[PDB]
Image (tube, rainbow, N blue to C red; front, side, top):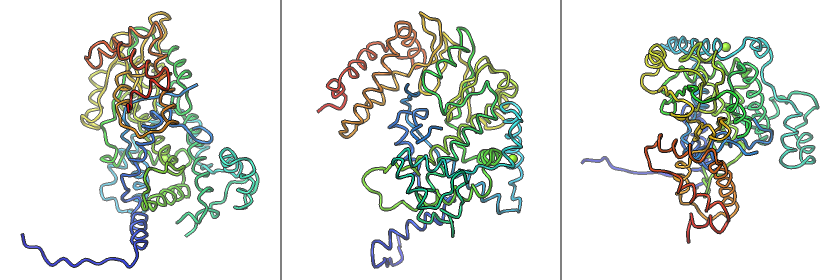
Length: 464
Ligand SMILES: [Mg+2]
């Protein structure tokens, strides 16, 4: 090997190197984004036990749906912003027209089979704008009612008036108004959840604001013994290899009121935390700007989940008694796959999305790391967390944290209460054996309940 002479050069101060690295990642967002963003997402999802339990905002959107399946998030928001730049510029159609035709057809299927047409005109003439009242109530929910008074008087906020954009973005960049920007983008997610709920048909449910019991009420009413349940597994399908998926989410976001001034605010805010790469610290800071992007990513992922179901199922989704969506997980009641349905899923995404047929009682439907089982005493269907996935998750080595250990124990205590319902334990062990081809899980249910009983017993999981 013949190498040319290597002569390196450096800056006079390490702080100049820190700023250069942060400025580079800031200047090249959203073209590239560090995988530490999605890695911080995964660390937060795994900590709070799944997507539905990842609701800890000041104002959201009785425990939540807790899943032990490890998270593998992808920066869907970054790809949406990339599609916004390729659309604002690049008027030259470099075969982005077939991407445009595909995304247009996706929005067509989404509207035809999953939506009403009542609110599209209102959202077009009234884009999403966050008012002074929300951002003041947002800070009041965190730092007290008085700190919200200083919040409004510091940034000169007028009551019952939309927060002017010139207060936190100019020349863009967040101009030292970090708590105002974070407050604004928390209201965008709240309005996006409210507006999506308004357009979706009543038989189509998104699990943003839904407790475990409130979701069980929907399951108990619509899911009976012998009822077929369809499932579209999209977890293995990467959205980045479809520019139409990112363009589809962008169009639906725009259809909901995310106009160009809003996208510029979103791209500017999330290009700023990409400039918080260095210094790293010892652990993820788990900030509110990080959470806002996770929820926006989760929102777009959930919408694209409904889109995929709308195009594949067509009228079968519209006539379904009950269809639930959150993240990439979904169940659709009373639909059995056919040849024309499996073909549409094949010629569209190849063999990247599968169709799973399940029945209440014999082939247990799976949803958010849990089984849809029917109680053998009340004959009412419900969702029961996967005990095998919980056992796998409990093997993760963790540093000592007495507060988080109590949260993990109380979360396991709640899961064991559902496992030992006298009408659940039998059919649960049948479901685990049916799904995983393993031996009877009941002795593990016994052992897991031992750990959850007391704080002293939970210590045996970590040991000494
Ligand atoms: Mg549109």
